[PDB]
Length: 152
Ligand code: HEM
Image (cartoon, rainbow, N blue to C red):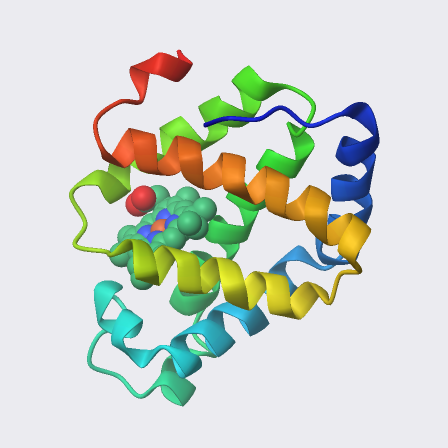
């Protein structure tokens, strides 16, 4: 279920994300590349990247736009870490286009893991981060399952 974060945990999340927030596009490009390189089956899910060698598409605007849009959502989630309804809305709106996409929870969770590994967080910030991410996926999966209105 959704579990609100304390004011202290909210600060921990903001601080944990700070490095990435300060280099959002750069981080996005690297993480997305590492994600598709470690879990190559996922490249085909992105119709614009499908059929090309990963090292070939990594430098294209298209690849960068995708990585950027993904991280922009996470950035806005962190922005709303202190407002559950707002946090939920960011995810609800983004969930729509994924509902009809043939993507497994494994794929989504693997991306979560690549992001976590890149942050190298200590356990205090990690706990707060995982609380926010658990909320992220609770909302995201509820929405993919057709139960997004509960957050309205
Ligand atoms: C859970 C973290 C994710 C976030 C925050 C996120 C966010 C977004 C956003 C904002 C868009 C653009 C609007 C649209 O839906 O067209 C998008 C598009 C898309 N996403 Fe995600 N996404 C995530 C994970 C994934 C995963 C794990 C996959 C599958 C490997 C995936 C596949 C796609 C595809 C195929 C598109 C559209 C293709 C395109 O625009 O060229 N996404 N995503």
